[PDB]
Picture 1 (cartoon, rainbow, N blue to C red):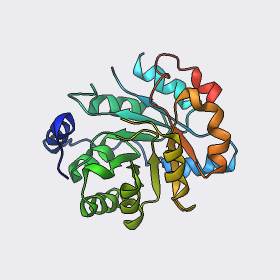
Picture 2: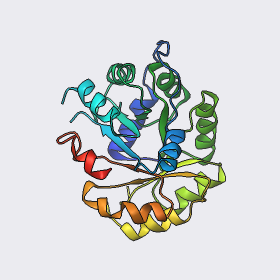
Picture 3: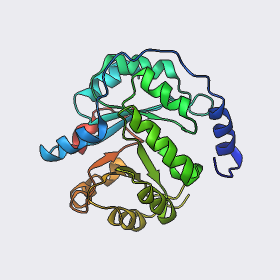
Picture 4: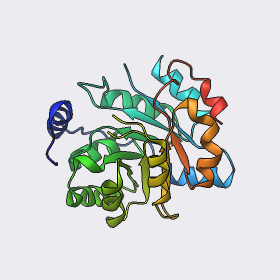
Length: 236
């Protein structure tokens, strides 16, 4: 990984030490990026719901299976209260795409994702060198997973495009300044053969129409839905 400090350094150091799991996968790959493109052809707004333990998780996942295009599950243990067991139980319970949302810094974590039933993984440009990211991209693709690559800024974008990413998520706040104009700028700079995901707050739902016209294919939510799951219906 790159030079890191503070909690982010701590979580990457712990992630490098994550023991591998010897699990056998219980489902096929249910591709997230491909289902987003299907929802786009069906004119159904494509919302990636989330689970982060801070709500019976299975009942929640089954609710979301009815509405969401996919489900992000936070599996980092020390700071975000996740687990591989929670991922596996949710993935075994539903047939929508599952994104393993963690700090993926070594190949064995992609092995873990595959063996536990996740359909893809998050990769974070700004914690990895370009060569590390390219290698992990290739490794994910060897399991039939197109990873969701997170960009922060134009330097991250340049890396992601140079290595041939086809599935990118863009937020509206630097990883702590919020800038919607900058989010739109980064979205515009991604070619149309890339599946693009915008982070969205539920309060921004009036922007979905325009963001779709600007090329966003799906929306990643990270607040409000666990307290009030039915809010996903109004996004859609």
